[PDB]
Length: 52
Length: 85
Image (cartoon, rainbow over all chains, first blue to last red; front, side):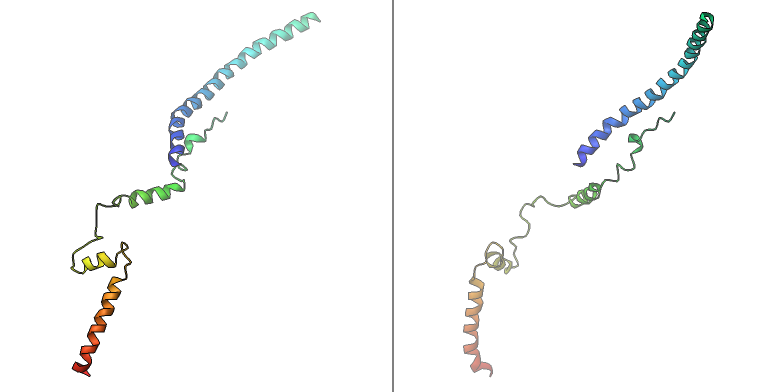
């Protein structure tokens, strides 16, 4: 029974560290995307005023 | 934003399991115990350990030493009355 618990934990220890890195890394890229959003926004507004 | 990880920060509860207490007990319990031994001390020679081996082991509950001891007392007191009292 004890062996069963242990075997799970071995594989976990490495692979979980991968996810740890991965999650924060994606979030960083997504931060940079906000600057893109601002490009989208200003242009949309400009077309609208001009249409009026 | 908070990337916190419970699984590998569980490593102080991975000593915490209850059968660990049994484990460290029974590696010590089984650090020297013979599997069943070879033939330890069931028979021995004290010259009455041989007597014990035939009658007073778990191998025999035979009533024979009782009989022997009884017959001894029957032989004893009849001669002895005239020698002591």
